[PDB]
Image (cartoon, rainbow, N blue to C red; front, side, top):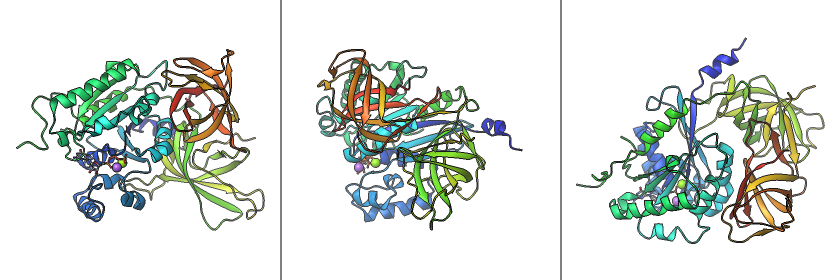
Length: 473
Ligand SMILES: Nc1nc2c(ncn2[C@@H]2O[C@H](COP(=O)(O)OP(=O)(O)OP(=O)(O)O)[C@@H](O)[C@H]2O)c(=O)[nH]1
Ligand SMILES: [Mg+2]
Ligand code: NA
């Protein structure tokens, strides 16, 4: 009836680029300007955005960043608070491809809320580290070994050890206009980062590159001296490098048919009013495999016990910052599509007394109705971690935060396997056990060769201690 095989063959190959950096770096601005350069923002829509920007703080706002800072609360505050996911598909990209651009907040409060988890949730092929090269800003942004830029590097430099894939880091030396493309300054900043990346974080030349730019003026983003690229610069533009990365990503082995279906619930809303049969609208990021309408699924909550059996009523494209068609129904969802998935669930019990609570970070899988997918609910969690630079050792009984997929939970360090050591130390590779502190909470873990289960351990103050993976066995 339906050719599952054919749908996968006509599915464009996606590349995901994740933008990272401190607040005020210019991530939202640059990324808004990029979208404009790719003709994803109409002239009419643009003029409306300048008007909005006129009514806001002229110290914080411009017409490009308001494209990404599109919530009422972010516009009044003047900085990003929520991660944005934009999928681009047009004739400026390689054929049969999509470019996913992800914005993340830099302000430390919302960085700790969303950004670290975005790295683990969306599993980007490319990191884009945006840096403010304006005078005094750069010097202020590297205070000690735990500055916010190094905290980013303490994660992305060490994820997915043993490779099978290689890292791709683009460092955007931004706001070059505010320094009139000071050659010796840009070279200095580049020299400094190059050393740290190589000596402290073990990056190799092929894995990264520097690109000077101005996200506001659009200098060197794509294709009498302002909005100019100086004569001495002979490197590539930002988008040219993005293009190549998407293109080289084309030659990637696609194992979708083999993969089991796994999806992460990014957002959930129960249609009102509630009834004997209820309909839940889920925003789902597909982690692996595929899902088609009419199939039976299982929703597993972070609330330790709850599990819901339901049927996929319909699926739609998720609402995006760019204009898309959310009216039409989709037959098939594929890794890494983000879809609206309407789930039909029949209440076993009285529907008024007991109402289900489906939260972000919960997973959805195909129903194991009565090769079956192994699913674990863990309170005591074994972790295969590796440390590097550590200011202070981490003793047993320490309280930590465990980042996994879209969730972060307080845990207690309860055991260090294979040794009588009483603490985690610098530059080690350990097997460790942590315990969920929160009552009636359990971490959902899928044991499969097609799921990474990367994690990050931080202190309560959100200082990265180690990177690792859930050890299921
Ligand atoms: N002169 C100049 N200013 C820029 C440039 N890019 C961004 N800005 C300004 O820098 C400020 C911060 O820009 P944002 O786009 O909000 O940077 P951000 O990294 O997204 O900030 P967060 O969302 O808080 O992480 C804004 O007031 C912009 O007008 C640039 O290329 N040149
Ligand atoms: Mg922003
Ligand atoms: Na900002």
